[PDB]
Amino acid sequence: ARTKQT
Amino acid sequence: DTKLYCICKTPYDESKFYIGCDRCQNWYHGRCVGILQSEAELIDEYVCPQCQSTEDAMTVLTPLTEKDYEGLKRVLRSLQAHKMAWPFLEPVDPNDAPDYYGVIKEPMDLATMEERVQRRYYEKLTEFVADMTKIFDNCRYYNPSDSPFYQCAEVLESFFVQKLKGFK
Ligand SMILES: [Zn+2]
Ligand SMILES: [Zn+2]
């Protein structure tokens, strides 16, 4: 899954 | 970036965890869609709640495929073999039901549905469900609520609804 993290 | 993301419609916050939906390509805060960051690691393709809801509602409106038709035949046959299905196997005989056709304006039975399946009459699942529902609604309209016929309709419809779960 594609994600955005800090 | 001035785009409002997620269901909460807010600007991108670099400090927060987001997961992307492969269906709509929007981005969602993990917390807003119930996904934990550690959990996302084990997810391949992701579909957000709203898209999943639309896909679920869509199932009865999409074109029926040949595989869908093999399924319809399977469902019909399970209904025809059900113990409570005997009153709905064939068109009602006027001699067995007084003024039936004067009470029921749109008769339907399992044999008529089997014929429709055979000639690919249905184009959407909603149409198949509508005919089946007609069978049960006609029975409950013509027969009193305490008659076994009425109960057979209640039982079969409950059985039918379960049979359709996860159809497409
Ligand atoms: Zn959010
Ligand atoms: Zn989506």
Image (tube, grey):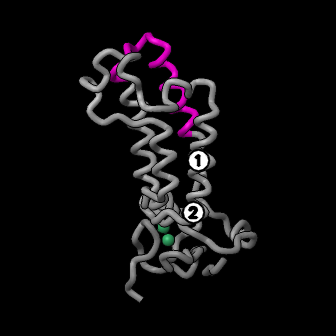
Between B87 and B29, the residue placed more toward the observer is B87
- Residue density around tag 2, few if under 14, some if 14–19, many if 20 or more, within 10 Å: few
Q: Give the quarter of the figure containing the N terminus of chain B.
A: bottom left
Where's the C terminus of chain B, which quadrant?
A: bottom right
Q: Position of residue B77 (x, y in %)?
A: 61, 42
Question: In the image, what residue occupies the spot 63% across and 63% down?
Answer: B35
> Residue at label 2?
B31
Region in magenta: B140-161
Tag 1's secondary structure?
loop
What subunit carries mark 2?
B
Which amino acid type is marked by label 2?
Arg
Q: Amino acid at mark 1?
A: Lys
Question: Where in the figure is residue B27, as x and y percent of width and height?
Answer: 51, 76
B147 magenta-colored: yes
Between residue B130 and residue B47, name the one nearer to us.
B130
Residue at the extreme top:
B146
User: Within 8 Å: ligand 1 and the Cβ of disc 2?
Assistant: yes
* First in sequence: mark 1 vs mark 2: 2
Q: Residue at x 53, y 39 (%)?
A: B161
Q: Nearer the viewer, residue B38 or B129?
A: B129
Of circles 1 and 2, the one toward us is: 1
Give neighbour class at mark 1: few <14, some 14-19, many 20+ (Cα, 10 Å): few
- Image point 70% across, 70% down: which residue? B43
From the image, tell me which residue sits under label 1. B165
Quadrant in which residue B75 is drawn: top right
Residue B23 vs B56, above or below: the answer is below
| Left-right relation of B112 to B72 | left
The answer to whether one can see residue B38 in this image is yes
User: Mark 2 and mark 1 in contact (Cβ < 8 Å)?
Assistant: no
